[PDB]
Each structure stands twice: as C-alpha cells, then as structure tokens.
Image (cartoon, coloured by chain):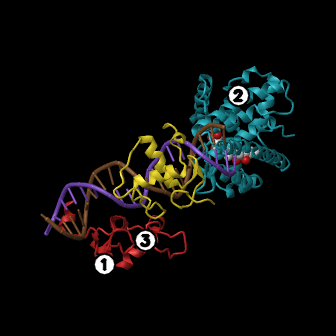
Chain colours: A yellow, B cyan, C red, D purple, E brown
DNA sequence: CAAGGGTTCAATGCACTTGT
DNA sequence: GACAAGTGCATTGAACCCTT
C-alpha cells in the first residue's frame, strides 16, 4: 500500500528502516555491500523520483540516508 | 535437510536391484507359458502370467530386510494380503498411455477389449483408471521400490507381532521421506509428494477387493482359477 | 530555445537519430534488441500506457509501439548488407 | 500466512568500437 | 570529424528464497 519515501515508486514494505521500493532497496544494498562512493555531476540536489532516480547515484544514495536507511541494517553477503 | 545412512542407501540400492531383478519372469518360464504358434486363450495367458507375477512378488518380499524376522504365520499373512496389491503397482509400471493398454512380459499389449473376452471385463475399467493416475504421477524406481516394500509390511489383520511389522515398515516409510526430501528442495511440496504417494496405498486396497470379487465371480462362473491363486487370495 | 534534445519515445535526453528517429540510448538499445529477437510483447495494463522514464521499463509492448509510431525503422536494424554477411 | 533479511539474472542502458 | 550503427558488460529491480 505504501510509497517509497525516497522516490515515490510503490514500496514493497520497509527495507533497512524505511518504506522503499525494490529499486531503492537493491541500490542501497549494493552501495553498502561494495562500499561504493559516488560523485554528483551537478550540485548534489538532483531530482530522485520514480522517473529519473537512475540519473544520479550520489543523490539517490544521499536520499536513502536522509529518508532514514541504515547502513548497519545491510548484512554481510550470504 | 539431511542425507541418508549407509543402511538406507544400501537398501534403496538393494531394492532398486531386486525390483529389476524381478520385474519379469525368467526367459524360460516366460518361454514355457507363452508357447504357441475360444475364450480360454486370453484367459489362459492372463491367469498363467498372473501366477508368475505373484511368484516374483513373493520372492521379492523375502529379499526384504526384516522379513525373515517374521513368524511363518505372519509372513504368509503379510504376503497373502500384499500379493494382490503389489501386483497392482506392477501393472502400473507396464501401462502404455499411448494405447491405454497393459503390456505383458511377452511384449504383448492387452486392451480393455482383451480383458473383456477373457471374462475379466469387470476388473479392467478401474485397473486402467488407476494406471492413468499412476502415469501422471510420474514416479521414479526408488519410489516404486520403497512403496512396494511399505505395502508388504502394511498392517494386516491376523498379525501376531503387529507392533513389530509397524516398525519394520516405519523404516521404509522413513527412508522414502528422506529420499523425497533430498530429490527436491526440502520445501512445502516435499510433503505433497510424500502424501500423494502414501495415497496410492488406499487406492490399492480398492483394487485388491476387486481382484478378489473377480476371483469369486470366476469360481462362480465355474472357471478354474489356478489353485495357486485360489489359495493365496483366500478365494473360497 | 532547445534546452534539451528529447527522445520522441520517452522524453529522456536524446543522444542522436537512431533508425531514423530522435531517441535516447535506452530506446535505441531496446528497439534494436526487440527487432533482432522479433520479440512479441503483451501489455499487462490497458494497452495504452503513456511512455516516460518510469513506464518505459514497465511496459515493453507500449514502448515498442511508441518506437514504431515515432518512425523507428525496423528494416534498418541489421539489414542484409556486406557488414552483416561479415559477423 | 506476513515482514524484512537474503539472492538471482534477464533486461537494461551507459560507454564504448566500427564503419562511412 | 561527427555521426549512427553495432558491442561489451556493470547496474537495475521484480521476483524469488529464508528465518523469525
Ligand atoms: C484374477 C487374476 C487372474 C486377475 C489379475 C489381472 O486382473 C491383472 C492385474 O490385470 C494381471 C493379468 C496378467 C498380469 O498378471 C501380468 C501379466 C504380465 O505379463 C506381467 C508379468 C510380470 O512382469 C509383472 O511384474 C507385470 C505384468 C504386466 C503382470 C501385472 C498384473 C496383470 C496385468
């Protein structure tokens, strides 16, 4: 029923602390697992919605953080 | 999500071996009965072939772990009740969906029409339905061997050490559980499979009574049912 | 005036003319893949999805219909020229 | 069963190479 | 060159599995 708090896509439930879609779930997992750092090619205020969330990895990750996603909730690879 | 002991696999192995060891009657026996280059012909073959089937079924039963631990009284008790029900598992294995017929050990296909002629017209419509149901079941030779074993140590009336057999059976019942638990992800469907299989037991009980009624409705038609069969199925 | 060259299919930033239509890399690749496989898609909605950056990933049937409607030429995807007899 | 951890892998799309 | 067609492959995310 819920919406992803990051992008507005249909949430599949809570993930890593926040209501979020499979997209943002999968993205946050891969970012934390690999310990990736991104660089915005704009002004670090890019639009992150259901339409253009894939345009800026830095801004998508920062928005996961601001929404309340917890790096600690991401477990070791199994 | 465990595997199986050595016993278990030695048994499964063993059972899969005896099964092929006895699926058909020897080349000489088969040759002797099938000699020949009028409603007594289909009748003779069907009845004569059944006497071979039963024999094989009996010997297989003795090649079973724990069987010799049974009182001769019980042994003839278990065997006497299983004879007709296993013979059922074995007609399923030689059923051909393409022709809806049963294939005798001499490679001949017997249709619902042949069983008519021989006066077995009563037993066939149901026997063939059970085959179609065992077909879509799609079972492997382990199942079939294990299942068979089970049927044999199935609780029967007249049993002296009833509680004994129950366990001699609990083993095979258990082995089957495991083998199914490995062959597929020990997931939900794992029981669903174990169940449909154990269900074969109850259907095999209905086809057993029909075989008996056929023996009856045959003695009554004054038609010599081999003494051997009349004896083993308690056909009065 | 022209602040951004627009993909005629989805409205994403167009990278150039692909198979005779101003399209993004996403729609270019989707169209080429759809044509080379001769893919037949089945919309699981109402057979009338408006294409954007969200819906383009959601409905392959309507995206392909939009690619054609915009003027993408399927005959221009790996035609039988000398270069193809190569690979 | 549901939730929220996990994983998978075909489709995707960015960056590239090839041909004119 | 600059463009458009073709290619390589890392990333995406819908659909699963697993444990509480
Ligand atoms: C009353 C009694 C005679 C009736 C029994 C009938 O209804 C049955 C069940 O229909 C009988 C008739 C003949 C029959 O004994 C057989 C012939 C074979 O050739 C073979 C011999 C041997 O390879 C068996 O492992 C399988 C099979 C196909 C058996 C199965 C049971 C059959 C098919």
Q: Nearer the viewer, residue B127 or A75?
A: A75
The local crowd at label 2, few if under 14, some if 14 to 19, many if 20 or more residues have their Cα within 10 Å, is some
At x 41%, y 75%, the residue is C66
Count of numbered labels shown in the rendering: 3
Q: Left or right of B184: which side holds E4? A: left
Task: In the rendered view, tell whether residue B19 sits above or below residue B89.
Answer: above
At x 62%, y 23%, the residue is B7
Q: Secondary structure at mark 3?
A: helix
Q: Left or right of E13: which side holds E1? A: left
Q: Nearer the viewer, residue B145 or B211?
A: B145
- Return the residue at label 2: B171
Q: Secondary structure at mark 1?
A: loop
- Return the residue at label 1: C1
Q: Are marks 1 and 3 in contact (CB under 8 Å)?
A: no
Residue mark closest to the camera, 1 vs 2 = 1
Identify the image quadrant of the N terminus of chain B.
top right
Residue B160 lies, in percent from the top left, at 85, 25
The local crowd at label 1, few if under 14, some if 14 to 19, many if 20 or more residues have their Cα within 10 Å, is few
How far apart are the alpha carbons under marks 2 and 3? 60 Å
How far apart are the alpha carbons under marks 1 and 2? 83 Å
Q: Nearer the viewer, residue A22 or A45?
A: A45
- Return the residue at label 3: C63
Residue B210 lies, in percent from the top left, at 80, 48
At x 57%, y 38%, the residue is B183
At x 28%, y 76%, the residue is C20
Q: Are marks 1 and 2 in contact (CB under 8 Å)?
A: no
């Amino acid at each position: 029923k819920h919406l992803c708090s990051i992008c507005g896509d249909r949430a599949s439930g809570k993930h890593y602390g926040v209501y979020s879609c499979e997209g943002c779930k999968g993205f946050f997992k891969r970012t934390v697992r690999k310990d990736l750092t991104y660089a915005c090619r704009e002004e670090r205020n890019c639009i992150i919605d259901k339409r253009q969330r894939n345009r800026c990895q830095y801004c998508r990750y920062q928005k996961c953080l601001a929404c309340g996603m917890k790096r600690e909730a991401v477990q070791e690879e199994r | 999500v465990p595997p199986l002991t050595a016993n278990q696999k030695s048994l499964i192995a063993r059972l899969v071996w005896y099964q092929e060891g006895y699926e058909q009657p020897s080349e000489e026996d088969l040759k002797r009965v099938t000699q020949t280059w009028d409603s007594d012909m289909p009748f003779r073959q069907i009845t004569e072939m059944t006497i071979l089937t039963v024999q094989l079924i009996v010997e297989f039963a003795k090649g079973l772990p724990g069987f010799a631990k049974i009182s001769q009284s019980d042994q003839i008790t278990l065997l006497k009740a299983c004879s007709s029900e296993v013979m059922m598992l074995r007609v399923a294995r030689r059923y051909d969906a393409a022709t809806d017929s049963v294939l005798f050990a001499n490679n001949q296909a017997y249709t619902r029409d042949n069983y008519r002629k021989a006066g077995m017209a009563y037993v066939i419509e149901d026997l063939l339905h059970f085959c179609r149901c065992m077909y879509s079941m799609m079972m492997d030779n382990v199942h079939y061997a294990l299942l068979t074993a089970i049927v044999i140590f199935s609780d029967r009336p007249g049993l002296e050490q009833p509680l004994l057999v129950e366990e001699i059976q609990r083993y095979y019942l258990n082995t089957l559980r495991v083998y199914i638990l490995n062959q597929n992800s020990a997931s939900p469907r794992c029981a669903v499979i174990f169940g449909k299989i154990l269900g074969i037991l109850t259907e095999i009980r209905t086809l057993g009574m029909q075989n008996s009624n056929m023996c009856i409705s045959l003695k009554l038609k004054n038609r010599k049912l081999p003494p051997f069969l009349e004896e083993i199925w308690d056909v009065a | 005036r022209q602040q951004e060259e627009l993909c005629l299919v989805c409205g994403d930033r167009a990278s150039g003319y692909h198979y005779n239509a101003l399209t993004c890399e996403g729609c270019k690749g989707f169209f080429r893949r759809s044509v080379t496989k001769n893919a037949v898609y089945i919309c699981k909605f109402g057979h009338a999805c408006e294409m954007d950056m969200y819906m383009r990933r959601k409905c392959q049937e309507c995206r392909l219909k939009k690619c054609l409607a915009v003027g993408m030429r399927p005959e221009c995807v790996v035609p039988e020229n000398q270069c193809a007899m190569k690979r």
